[PDB]
Amino acid sequence: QVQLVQSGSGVKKPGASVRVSCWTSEDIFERTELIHWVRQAPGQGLEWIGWVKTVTGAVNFGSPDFRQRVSLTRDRDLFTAHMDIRGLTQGDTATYFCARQKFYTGGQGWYFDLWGRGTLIVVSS
Amino acid sequence: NLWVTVYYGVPVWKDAETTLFCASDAKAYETEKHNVWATHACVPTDPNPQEIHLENVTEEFNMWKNNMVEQMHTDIISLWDQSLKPCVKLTPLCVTLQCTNVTNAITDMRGELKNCSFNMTTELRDKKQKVYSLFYRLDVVQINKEYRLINCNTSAITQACPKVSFEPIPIHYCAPAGFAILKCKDKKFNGTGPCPSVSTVQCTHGIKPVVSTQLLLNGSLAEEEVMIRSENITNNAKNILVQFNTPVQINCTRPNNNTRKSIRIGPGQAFYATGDIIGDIRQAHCNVSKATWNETLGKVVKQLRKHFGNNTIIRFANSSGGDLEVTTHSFNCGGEFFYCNTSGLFNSTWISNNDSITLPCRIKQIINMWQRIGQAMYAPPIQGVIRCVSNITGLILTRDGGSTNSTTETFRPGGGDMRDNWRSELYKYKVVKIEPLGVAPTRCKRRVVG
Amino acid sequence: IRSENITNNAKNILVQFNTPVQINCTRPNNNTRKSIRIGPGQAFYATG
Amino acid sequence: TLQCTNVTNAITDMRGELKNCSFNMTTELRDKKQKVYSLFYRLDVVQ
Amino acid sequence: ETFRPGGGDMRDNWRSELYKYKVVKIEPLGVAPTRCKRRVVG
Amino acid sequence: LGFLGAAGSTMGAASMTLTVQARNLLSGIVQIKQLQARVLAVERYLRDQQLLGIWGCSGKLICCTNVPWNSSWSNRNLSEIWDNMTWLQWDKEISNYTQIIYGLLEESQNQQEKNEQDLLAL
Amino acid sequence: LGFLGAAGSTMGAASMTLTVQARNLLSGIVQIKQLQARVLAVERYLRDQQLLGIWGCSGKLICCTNVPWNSSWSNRNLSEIWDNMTWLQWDKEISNYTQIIYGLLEESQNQQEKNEQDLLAL
Amino acid sequence: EIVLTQSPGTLSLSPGETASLSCTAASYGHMTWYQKKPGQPPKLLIFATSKRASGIPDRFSGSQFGKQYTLTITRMEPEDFARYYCQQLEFFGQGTRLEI
Ligand SMILES: *[C@@H]1O[C@H](CO)[C@@H](O[C@@H]2O[C@H](CO)[C@@H](O[C@@H]3O[C@H](CO[C@H]4O[C@H](CO)[C@@H](O)[C@H](O)[C@@H]4O)[C@@H](O)[C@H](O)[C@@H]3O)[C@H](O)[C@H]2NC(C)=O)[C@H](O)[C@H]1NC(C)=O
Ligand SMILES: *[C@@H]1O[C@H](CO)[C@@H](O[C@@H]2O[C@H](CO)[C@@H](O[C@@H]3O[C@H](CO)[C@@H](O)[C@H](O)[C@@H]3O)[C@H](O)[C@H]2NC(C)=O)[C@H](O)[C@H]1NC(C)=O
Ligand SMILES: *[C@@H]1O[C@H](CO)[C@@H](O[C@@H]2O[C@H](CO)[C@@H](O)[C@H](O)[C@H]2NC(C)=O)[C@H](O)[C@H]1NC(C)=O
Ligand SMILES: *[C@@H]1O[C@H](CO)[C@@H](O[C@@H]2O[C@H](CO)[C@@H](O)[C@H](O)[C@H]2NC(C)=O)[C@H](O)[C@H]1NC(C)=O
Ligand SMILES: *[C@@H]1O[C@H](CO)[C@@H](O[C@@H]2O[C@H](CO)[C@@H](O)[C@H](O)[C@H]2NC(C)=O)[C@H](O)[C@H]1NC(C)=O
Ligand SMILES: *[C@@H]1O[C@H](CO)[C@@H](O[C@@H]2O[C@H](CO)[C@@H](O)[C@H](O)[C@H]2NC(C)=O)[C@H](O)[C@H]1NC(C)=O
Ligand SMILES: *[C@@H]1O[C@H](CO)[C@@H](O[C@@H]2O[C@H](CO)[C@@H](O)[C@H](O)[C@H]2NC(C)=O)[C@H](O)[C@H]1NC(C)=O
Ligand SMILES: *[C@@H]1O[C@H](CO)[C@@H](O[C@@H]2O[C@H](CO)[C@@H](O)[C@H](O)[C@H]2NC(C)=O)[C@H](O)[C@H]1NC(C)=O
Ligand SMILES: *[C@@H]1O[C@H](CO)[C@@H](O[C@@H]2O[C@H](CO)[C@@H](O)[C@H](O)[C@H]2NC(C)=O)[C@H](O)[C@H]1NC(C)=O
Ligand SMILES: *[C@@H]1O[C@H](CO)[C@@H](O[C@@H]2O[C@H](CO)[C@@H](O)[C@H](O)[C@H]2NC(C)=O)[C@H](O)[C@H]1NC(C)=O
Ligand SMILES: *[C@@H]1O[C@H](CO)[C@@H](O[C@@H]2O[C@H](CO)[C@@H](O)[C@H](O)[C@H]2NC(C)=O)[C@H](O)[C@H]1NC(C)=O
Ligand SMILES: *[C@@H]1O[C@H](CO)[C@@H](O[C@@H]2O[C@H](CO)[C@@H](O)[C@H](O)[C@H]2NC(C)=O)[C@H](O)[C@H]1NC(C)=O
Ligand SMILES: *[C@@H]1O[C@H](CO)[C@@H](O[C@@H]2O[C@H](CO)[C@@H](O)[C@H](O)[C@H]2NC(C)=O)[C@H](O)[C@H]1NC(C)=O
Ligand SMILES: *[C@@H]1O[C@H](CO)[C@@H](O[C@@H]2O[C@H](CO)[C@@H](O)[C@H](O)[C@H]2NC(C)=O)[C@H](O)[C@H]1NC(C)=O
Ligand SMILES: *[C@@H]1O[C@H](CO)[C@@H](O[C@@H]2O[C@H](CO)[C@@H](O)[C@H](O)[C@H]2NC(C)=O)[C@H](O)[C@H]1NC(C)=O
Ligand SMILES: *[C@@H]1O[C@H](CO)[C@@H](O)[C@H](O)[C@H]1NC(C)=O
Ligand SMILES: *[C@@H]1O[C@H](CO)[C@@H](O)[C@H](O)[C@H]1NC(C)=O
Ligand SMILES: *[C@@H]1O[C@H](CO)[C@@H](O)[C@H](O)[C@H]1NC(C)=O
Ligand SMILES: *[C@@H]1O[C@H](CO)[C@@H](O)[C@H](O)[C@H]1NC(C)=O
Ligand SMILES: *[C@@H]1O[C@H](CO)[C@@H](O)[C@H](O)[C@H]1NC(C)=O
Ligand SMILES: *[C@@H]1O[C@H](CO)[C@@H](O)[C@H](O)[C@H]1NC(C)=O
Ligand SMILES: *[C@@H]1O[C@H](CO)[C@@H](O)[C@H](O)[C@H]1NC(C)=O
Ligand SMILES: *[C@@H]1O[C@H](CO)[C@@H](O)[C@H](O)[C@H]1NC(C)=O
Ligand SMILES: *[C@@H]1O[C@H](CO)[C@@H](O)[C@H](O)[C@H]1NC(C)=O
């Protein structure tokens, strides 16, 4: 149950961009196949956003709205990952989480073994 | 009354893994004694046809669990690294570069050509020389006039030996004695599940170590129909192998009589770098038949609907982003390394109920093979002429994610994991071990004589 | 008490206790570390 | 060649065990030099 | 008599654990007398 | 039939090819990874030969013993087994008792026959 | 008695375990100095089989010859040897007789019997 | 049609009795389970195979038939009161809450 190091929280104006980051140990990073991002707005259930492949940088998103407004990157030498969100709206106020999967084969299903504490992004006037 | 009998030589096998023997065509070695995949020594190709058709025998296959893929992958890497290990040790080469764009060029303002001269060592410790070696933009970064090689903070930049050919050489894999390789004869096989008919062969055949990213090149074709193969359908983490039943021809070329300069940077320490370029300079590119591409995709679409329904829409799109290697199609031709923009191939939507496509390309000389961290190979320049003809045999695709309000699905190029290339040839085979001990009931009681 | 001989002082004696003697050893104090490249990717570690 | 003196402005335990030393070290580029600093134990160095 | 710490030869450490063990080889061939004549039928 | 071609035939019919199977690399003979493979093939071969020596079956492809067959492990007729089954199917049905049968062969047949012969020899 | 458990028993009693000893890695079978060790075990195993083949004793744990025992080799009683001694002691007792005995077995029995049998076969 | 749905929804519990939650889904994917308390990141409870996750104090188990998976929570202990979510690949259920 190792916690991932999560970047700090903050408040942004509508239309602003924001970067969210997380870090882990080199042993955890190397073992991780995928880094996933998920979101939870207050009063809402958990929503999957997308993932970035730790080896090739390939990206797979959920709703196309995220594809246009969100970019995911990774850096294998720093054992970190970053999420860049642009065009922020009041509806994007939510807790965002960094999560990792180390399951490598079909039939195992998706897992999130490791989680960051998550961070809050507030969008307002 | 029945008794125990023993039968040596019983034709029974069990699933097993063992290291396979490398076999290859010795003639390839004779023509290219320094070829990377041409074993100095090897087992003969053993082209002889299967003696056994295993009539009325069926067997279960699972290409996704087939570890012979890992053996192929491991050996390709090991051979690559050893053949280039002693070549030059150019890591000391990196110095501050100071320069501006090429001027008085004929051109095609492309920022691709950089004319750079930097201080460098000589055969004598006490003497220095100016190199004046050209570089591609992709291989350098700004410290804006000051430049550095892009991989300079990696452990070393090493030139590939100029004598070593990188042309793929067919590699056959042969069983150790007491082991055998089974081959599935089922037409249009998914590469998984029970095979209706199998055969036994001493070796695999026709496999080549062709390295490519988005497109599968010079591989085997399906006998009847385009096959859609994947570890699963619902898991978007997994890649899809398209497996064409027909080739699509693609031509690629590069301009224009780029000269080479030989520089000694120390005792016997040859270094090759790009010299001046004769005539005009045009962007490198590839050509795909448009008409052929339609028939090709139409067949793929018809097969995809079998998994998603006939009330669906199949949309294609260009890359999702990520490293240059996954976002572009890459290949090795003439010893030169190319990265190509394939978006011209995917701008279409397929709804149920002499022309060509030109794909621009770029060249860079510093390559980090197999996504290895901290190491890099410097390719020596190829002296002025690249001509390539190739057969596209499939694509590596991924399905887009998210919920839908419709029956539309979207597919993009993806993967970049080289092991998936190997799977396209190895899915037909399985490795098993033969057990020589069997016991059965009998009427005999072994009357003792003495 | 074990030895190759007991008269030859060149030889060592192995004492072989029948019980352990416990020891705590420690080292101060949050010494930091610095990572220095001394060449391309040539990481060198030194006390901060 | 290292050029240095004893560690100063330390909280301490004058023990001579530690020195604060600096030198001209190479960098990723043949053309550039850097000052590393850092600490050494007395046992690892000689005059 | 006076005793001091000494040695420093690491092989003495290994010996303190290995003294309990010995390596031998098994030799199957053997011969012994009996009353048998090896009767032969040809 | 050829090597393992017999696998599709009945157990009785398959016995015609036991020599052929012995010829087809069962011997462990291969015409640093390759070196290790050669050594392994030899070790596997010799192990099986040791078992035949232990059972008193050495030098023969087919060998009778005095050990009774545990029919409860098959629940089939003698002719049913020989004519209506392949060796691949058969091996699974009796795979659980390999260790038991092998132990019985040593104790009930081979060591005893040799000891009885020694009494006759003397 | 298990591997070498027989060493504590009399020579006669020990004969019951000869198969057990054959099973317990005498065979040379495994469950780059480690590779060389595997090769050596095989070479040692095959050599001993050859020697039995030369004697005509191959395939048997216990084998007789028409070569007479020399009472002067041990100066012990038949029952003394079998009941009052271990094999470890016995090996030491006749240890200098290996060269002569080994030669006699080949010359007096194996080559001779094969030639005489061939003549009967002609 | 919602790909993944969860039930019974929020329910009253009595410690000493064993609770159960379940979810259903389209296209036969594997299901896994997570739980969270306010202010905390979620924790993995149950694997696709029904195997207990590391760090789980032997109180969780489950099984499935067809399109439905059910999990049980031993003796409704108060330490386990949390929001619970069923997951299938990219989808999450609306979740449930354990109350006394
Ligand atoms: C991708 O991975 C998916 C997850 O592993 C695969 O889904 C599996 O697909 C098979 C075949 O359709 C399903 O098996 C069916 O099970 C139902 C009934 O329930 C079964 O299990 C219960 C509990 O042990 C048992 O009591 C029942 O008797 C059944 O054994 C049967 O009626 C069907 O005939 C069939 O057996 C798996 O259940 C299903 N797994 C899951 C988690 O949904 C999927 O097929 C994979 N995709 C590809 C392309 O391979
Ligand atoms: C080896 O050298 C390369 C090239 O200098 C290093 O890559 C560079 O790393 C820095 C730091 O992460 C990147 O800086 C970033 O620039 C963007 C530009 O807007 C800025 O927004 C970020 O906040 C950050 O400053 C830089 O772009 C990147 N260069 C390239 C070409 O990607 C690399 O990190 C070095 N290796 C190591 C291990 O240090
Ligand atoms: C890069 O710049 C160098 C330096 O100007 C070019 O080499 C010079 O070319 C002129 C042309 O007549 C000669 O007169 C100079 O003597 C050359 N320099 C030296 C050191 O001899 C070089 O050709 C340029 N390269 C490119 C690709 O433009
Ligand atoms: C090489 O060419 C590039 C492209 O023209 C130069 O970079 C540009 O320099 C002009 C000013 O002269 C700027 O206005 C552009 O925005 C620059 N382009 C960039 C930064 O992408 C470059 O300076 C020339 N040689 C160098 C930089 O050494
Ligand atoms: C790739 O280049 C080859 C030639 O090297 C092209 O083949 C020629 O195509 C023209 C089409 O009118 C024929 O007339 C020629 O006879 C062909 N030459 C041959 C067969 O040697 C080929 O079409 C090119 N491929 C693409 C996609 O342009
Ligand atoms: C790909 O197709 C283009 C367009 O047909 C080819 O470019 C032409 O090459 C001929 C050569 O004689 C020129 O005369 C044309 O003007 C070129 N067309 C252009 C530049 O638009 C290109 O060579 C083909 N690429 C191959 C075959 O690799
Ligand atoms: C590319 O370089 C080669 C030389 O390496 C050029 O070959 C020349 O071709 C002309 C043809 O009339 C001959 O007269 C020359 O003697 C050749 N030079 C040699 C053999 O060194 C070739 O022409 C060059 N291509 C271009 C486009 O310039
Ligand atoms: C792959 O798809 C992306 C869109 O998802 C393409 O994006 C275009 O990039 C060019 C160059 O920056 C822009 O001028 C266009 O406006 C972009 N289109 C958009 C944002 O819709 C991308 O070009 C495609 N392939 C590439 C860039 O190789
Ligand atoms: C891949 O090719 C497409 C099509 O040529 C590129 O999109 C064009 O990019 C240029 C600028 O470099 C724009 O002027 C064009 O209008 C774009 N065409 C469109 C948007 O249809 C795309 O950028 C290329 N991807 C690369 C180079 O990575
Ligand atoms: C692409 O596929 C075609 C079709 O299989 C290849 O052309 C065949 O090559 C073989 C071997 O020389 C010939 O026996 C066939 O008759 C050819 N088929 C024809 C001409 O229709 C072609 O060589 C392949 N291309 C590459 C680069 O491998
Ligand atoms: C060894 O014993 C000494 C003496 O008891 C320990 O030093 C003491 O550590 C405590 C820690 O709270 C201090 O309050 C005392 O003042 C220390 N005594 C001194 C400095 O004389 C020492 O830590 C022990 N070493 C171990 C346990 O490794
Ligand atoms: C030794 O170094 C570690 C950090 O590497 C120090 O850990 C800090 O502990 C405080 C306690 O509240 C935290 O607030 C800091 O955030 C921690 N540091 C980091 C980087 O997280 C530890 O306290 C240090 N010990 C001494 C004696 O200073
Ligand atoms: C070793 O010496 C260096 C250099 O004097 C010390 O680091 C300096 O500390 C002062 C005060 O904070 C800074 O103004 C200087 O810029 C620092 N120099 C460098 C290069 O960072 C260092 O603290 C000394 N180490 C000790 C005393 O342990
Ligand atoms: C594989 O299947 C074929 C077809 O069933 C077998 O052919 C048998 O041929 C013999 C000839 O005397 C007939 O008596 C059999 O009735 C045929 N089949 C059966 C099931 O009896 C063939 O023997 C099978 N396997 C082999 C031959 O190895
Ligand atoms: C080890 O020695 C003991 C004797 O000290 C052996 O015990 C024998 O047990 C049998 C059982 O019937 C008696 O008949 C013998 O008389 C006992 N021997 C003596 C000397 O009294 C024991 O069997 C020996 N170990 C082995 C493996 O034979
Ligand atoms: C070589 O070093 C000198 C040092 O003054 C510098 O001025 C010159 O530009 C360098 N030449 C290069 C980098 O080509
Ligand atoms: C491919 O898998 C599907 C899944 O049920 C199966 O029905 C089909 O027969 C398989 N086809 C082949 C050729 O293996
Ligand atoms: C591909 O085929 C479809 C259907 O005939 C056609 O509408 C489309 O224009 C074709 N694309 C081409 C020719 O590039
Ligand atoms: C280190 O190099 C600088 C020049 O870059 C030189 O002035 C200095 O004397 C050298 N070392 C010391 C201790 O000064
Ligand atoms: C065994 O085979 C014989 C001959 O076909 C048959 O009569 C007998 O009923 C069989 N026993 C069974 C099937 O148990
Ligand atoms: C062999 O016995 C084990 C239990 O010890 C059992 O699980 C297994 O299924 C049995 N195998 C067969 C073929 O009956
Ligand atoms: C027994 O020893 C005597 C010693 O002179 C020797 O002559 C005789 O041949 C030996 N017998 C055998 C069978 O070796
Ligand atoms: C065997 O015992 C008898 C007892 O009388 C003795 O005479 C004879 O010499 C013995 N044989 C030997 C010791 O070989
Ligand atoms: C073998 O020869 C040595 C030579 O002294 C002798 O001491 C020993 O007893 C002899 N052993 C046998 C079995 O004759």
Image (cartoon, coloured by chain):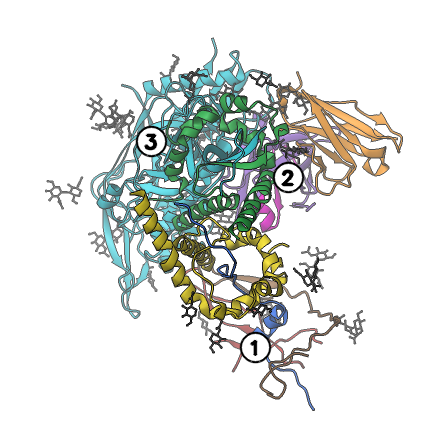
Chain colours: A purple, B cyan, C brown, D red, E blue, F green, G yellow, H orange
Mark closer to the observer (2, 3): 3
Category of crowding for the residue at label 1, using alpha-carbon neighbours closer than 10 angstroms: few (below 14), some (14–19), many (at least 20): few
Residue A27 falls inside the magenta stretch: yes
| Residue E22 appears anywhere in the view | yes
Q: Which residues are drawn in magenta?
A: A12-32
Q: Residue at x 65, y 34 (%)?
A: A38
Quadrant where the image shows the N terminus of chain G: bottom right
Mark closer to the observer (1, 3): 1
Q: CA distance from mark 2 to mark 3?
A: 39 Å
Kindly state the secondary structure of the residue where label 2 is placed: strand
Residue assigned mark 2:
A99
Chain bearing tag 3 is B
Residue assigned mark 1:
E9
Q: Amino acid at mark 3?
A: Asn
Q: Residue furthest top?
A: B353
Q: Amino acid at mark 2?
A: Ala
Q: Are marks 2 and 3 in contact (CB under 8 Å)?
A: no
Q: Is residue B25 above or below residue B191?
A: below
Q: Is residue H32 above or below residue A7?
A: above
Mark closer to the observer (1, 2): 1
Decide if ligand 10 comes within 8 Å of the CB at mark 3: yes
| Residue B142 appears anywhere in the view | no
Residue assigned mark 3:
B218
Asked if residue G66 lies left or right of residue A91, the reply is left
Residue A106 is situated, as x and y percent measured from the top left of the image, at: 57, 32
Residue B278 is situated, as x and y percent measured from the top left of the image, at: 20, 43
Q: Amino acid at mark 1?
A: Asp
Query: In this rendering, do the residues under marks 1 and 2 share a single chain?
Result: no
Q: Residue at x 56, y 49 (%)?
A: F115
Kindly state the secondary structure of the residue where label 3 is placed: loop
Q: Residue furthest bottom?
A: E1
Residue B239 falls inside the magenta stretch: no
